[PDB]
Structures are given as C-alpha cells and as structure tokens.
Image: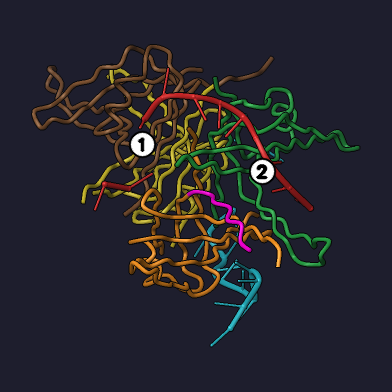
Chain colours: A yellow, B brown, C green, D orange, E red, F cyan
DNA sequence: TTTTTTTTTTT
DNA sequence: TTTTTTTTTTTTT
C-alpha cells in the first residue's frame, strides 16, 4: 500500500534524447527546470512506451510541459545513484504553450 | 514559476532525527519506503526533509513504520565525494508550502 | 491538452454500494469526508472497472483511504423541473485507490 | 485529518470576474475547461487573496492555466442549490501558461 | 437525488 | 447584466 506521484510543470532543458530498447520500445530522456522562491531546480525525466515517442517527437529545448510520474532512484556504478521522474503508462505528459 | 510537487504515501524507514540549527529551526530527516504491488504469472526509498512547523510535528509523532502522507518539493543537492567526484542527492522537501499527515 | 486530477485522503462515510451491470462491469459508490473550527467536506467518489470491485471489496464505513481520480459534474433535472449539478470524483483505470491503515 | 487537492490544466471559458470584499480583498472566479480525448469538463474555480488579483489581471477567454486548490461544496439559498468549486487560496497555486 | 466519516495540530 | 452565455487541440495504479 503506497503512493508515489510527482507532478512537474516546467521548461525542457535540452532537446530530448530518444533511445530504443532491444525489444524496440522507445525511452526518452529530458532535463526539466522548475523555479521557486528565484532558484532553478533541474529534474531528470525519463519517458517510456508511447509517451517516449510523443516526447521525442514534440518536445524541444525551451518547451513548457506538464509531467506526471513517479520517483525512482537508479543504481549505477562507474556506486552512484540517479533519482528520476519515470513517466510511463501510469503517468501523463502535456505540452503547453 | 513552474510546479514542483511530490506526493508520497509510505512507511517511515527508521526512527526520525530532529536537529535544531543555530537559527532555532527544526529540521528533521527521515527515509520513506513506498511500495508498488505487481502481478503476473517493488520498494522505493525516499529521503524526506521537514523544516519549520512540520519539522516539529514530524519529529514528535513519526516512528519506525509509521504510515504517512507527505507532500513536498523535489530538491537535488550537489556535493563532491571524498573520491573527488561530484555526486547528487535528491530529496523531498516538506515545509510550510507542503503538508504531512500521519496515517492510522 | 488538459489535466483533471483530484487527490483525497479521507474517511468513508458509509459502506460501499457496488452495482453490477449486465456487461459485468461494476460501479461502486461511496462518500468521503476530508477535514481541515474543524471543517468536514463530503465528496461523492465513484469507482469504475476493476477499482469498482476492489473498492467494493475493501472499503467500509470509517475506512481511511487515498483516492486519485478526475472531476466530473453531472447535470440533471430535479422534480421541481430545475437544473441541478452533482460534481463527483471519478476513479477509473487512470486513477488510484489505496486503503490506508 | 485529510487531504483535499485538485490540479487542473486547461483553458478559461470567459474573462474573469473579480469582486471586492468589505476588507478590500479580491475574489476572482472563472470557469475552466479540461478536455479528455472530444469530451470537455467545466470547472468552477474561485481564487482568493493575492492570486485573485493576479488571476483577475492576466487571465482572459482562452488563456491556458495551471490551477491547484481544494474542492469546496457551497450550499446556497427558493430552495437549496449546491455548487462544488475549486477554491484556490494561500494553500493553492496558479500558473499562467503559454 | 442528500447522512455519514474520523479525531495525537503568512502553502 | 451572468447562474454557469463558454474554452481550446502540436494526436490502455
């Protein structure tokens, strides 16, 4: 019994990087900036499945986007950890502007 | 500008730590485990930080294995490890702009 | 391009009502109380699909529950002939339900 | 002990209406359209304090907006009529988009 | 088409 | 000047 939800509205940092799995499923990375206080926070968002395809085709540097997903910390050595907002079938993405 | 919102429901990993800093502020850190339950024929760990009033309420009531609702913001803190290399810790900051609700 | 999301943590006011349709799709109705002196807001939450059966199985009066859904306002003509409006929280495959406690 | 949270991103139906209470504080109301792919949903949003002024000043028919608030059902009144509104106050948030 | 639930505190 | 006069589309927990 848990909940793990993240909601972001911000600007795409650089043009998305789309990659494809051995099974051919797209996965797309962006960085995403939100501002508070004025302070900029950078988020690593990774899209999977159909939304990865929509991300890489429609987002550019500067895009304002809404993003809904869940937090997962990815373990990767050479021991380091990247916390990412994972956007898949249980989440959402909407291009604004 | 922008929106930076995190909503978690999970169990507190360990007894909370409350620390008061020279400015008189409570800051309490916990870890939080959120679990998703699969099916075919699991666990995520979050670092949460309370400041201010909710820091006081967190330190008082939360214990090992308390169920809690947490609403905060994402914050990633850069730091150089002892090996010289930069590393990154992403936390969930819960302050006056957030919200906490003990559950049960 | 739109977002329509509701998130509630609250207490069920009474036992669920799960209604099955000829198709075998279930619909489950509850009301749900959230409190901010103390001030209680009552929500009408309706579950569709699998989550209708899961809510029907697991929610009871007094249950503390998290729900994530979407807002839906239903228009209807009252016996007085006048337009009325019921705004509900719709929980279906795009939503979530987690029994708390 | 509860949570009562609403998050909408959609488009304003018409120009905001803003009024002033005795104490001088603004209150802005709008309707907001959210569309699901085809089928539109209309929400009644009410802003209080600071955000009411901001909403009053920069929102107009068709403005794309992010809104964060709480649900509140207000019984009014010649019998009773109940409206459920999205109340955006100090605890909420609003972001103009585009 | 209208009753309730629950109760460990300057977004 | 109204009781929601309508908005606006860069597409299966």
Q: Are marks 2 and 1 in contact (CB under 8 Å)?
A: no
Distance Cα–Cα, label 2 vs label 1: 27 Å
C12 over D75 or under it: above or below: above
In which quadrant of the rendered image does the N terminus of chain B lie? Answer: bottom left
**Boundaries of the magenta span:** D70-77
Q: Which residue is mark 1?
A: B72
Task: Please name whichever residue, F11 or B73, is drawn nearer the observer in this view of the structure.
Answer: B73
Residue D97: x %, y % from top left: 41, 62
Residue sitting at 45 percent across and 37 percent down?
A19
- Say left or right for C14 vs B2: right
**Residue D37's image quarter?**
bottom right
Residue C44: numbered disc: 2
Q: Are marks 2 and 1 on the same chain?
A: no
Residue sitting at 55 percent across and 46 percent down?
C5
Mark 2 burial class by Cα count in 10 Å: few <14, some 14-19, many 20+: some
Asked whether residue D33 is drawn in magenta, I would say no
Tag 2, which chain?
A: C
Of tags 2 and 1, the one toward the viewer is 2
Q: Secondary structure at mark 1?
A: strand
Residue D45: x %, y % from top left: 51, 60
- In the displayed image of the protein, which residue is found farthest to the right? C22
Main SS of residues in magenta: strand
């Amino acid at each position: 019994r848990g909940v793990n939800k993240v909601i972001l509205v911000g600007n795409v940092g650089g043009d998305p990087e789309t990659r494809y799995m051995p099974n051919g499923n797209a996965v797309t990375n962006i960085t995403l900036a939100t501002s508070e206080s004025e302070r900029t926070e950078w988020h690593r968002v990774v899209f999977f499945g159909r939304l990865a395809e929509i991300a890489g085709e429609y987002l550019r540097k500067g895009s304002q986007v809404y993003v809904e997903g869940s937090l997962r910390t990815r373990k990767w050595q050479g021991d380091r950890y990247t916390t990412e907002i994972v956007v898949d079938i249980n989440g959402n993405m909407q291009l604004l502007g």
